[PDB]
Amino acid sequence: EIQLMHNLGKHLNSMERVEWLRKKLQDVHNFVAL
């Protein structure tokens, strides 16, 4: 479980992660990797 993985896509399927990954980069991107 991660602080960004818990919200947005809690449960997923390979072709949902692929588009989720685009939003996931907009959610945390660099964030000082904190």
Image (cartoon, rainbow, N blue to C red):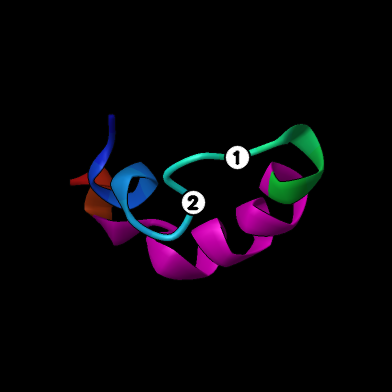
Of the pair 4 and 6, the residue shown nearer to us? 6
Decide: is 20 above or below 6.
below
| Secondary structure of residue under mark 2 | loop
Q: Percent from the top left, x then y, of residue 1?
A: 28, 29
Magenta segment, prevailing SS (helix, strand or loop)? helix
Of the pair 29 and 2, the residue shown nearer to us? 2
Q: Residue at x 58, y 66 (%)?
A: 23
Classify 10 Å Cα crowding around label 1: few (below 14), some (14-19), many (20 and above).
few
**Magenta extent:** 17-31
Decide: is 23 above or below 6.
below
Q: Percent from the top left, x then y, of residue 26?
A: 51, 70
Q: Is residue 8 inside the magenta stretch?
A: no
Q: How many marks?
A: 2
Q: Is residue 19 inside the magenta stretch?
A: yes
Give the labeled residue for mark 1.
Answer: 12
Farthest-out residue, left: 34
Marker disc for residue 9: 2
| Secondary structure of residue under mark 1 | loop
